[PDB]
Length: 208
Ligand SMILES: [Ca+2]
Image (cartoon, rainbow, N blue to C red):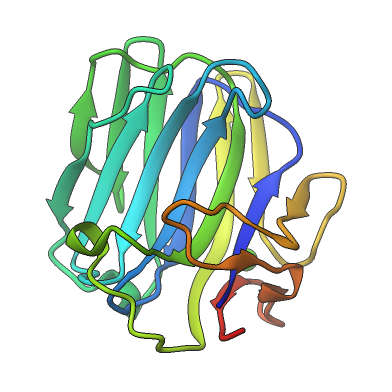
């Protein structure tokens, strides 16, 4: 299986991160929006996540890692099926808290051991292996898509607006030609990152 990952080339810090998206629906997969920096780049592993488990798109999972330590998973019920339309998901990341919102409504707050290292904005779609309890087993269904209409990052003195109508190499990069291995049971392919004519980033999960 081939999957997809899109990531910023720059780093961003504290502020409001918003994305308008529509995750894919299927057992065994995840569609995400998150920030990330790792020892892979050094720093210290700090990451804030919005993950949609395809097994049940009526919920969304929030989580974070501070210094390689995670386990802050919070599953919230949305009140609607996320895969049926675009909604706005955001997280307000400040030095002493992370606040998550759905369509402008506050849904979760965290104040413990909050990350502080600036990272890249990343979006991916992938199928797991060895985590059937978390994601359900992946059944090989495909192609599957996760779509993103726009991304916005607002700090108090700047705004990063990305409407996703075309590929901009100075700002983003596509993952390609490798697998994360581990529970990621797919290889990242640049060809699986496409832009629709109407201005949406469309990540796909396909066979091969
Ligand atoms: Ca757009």
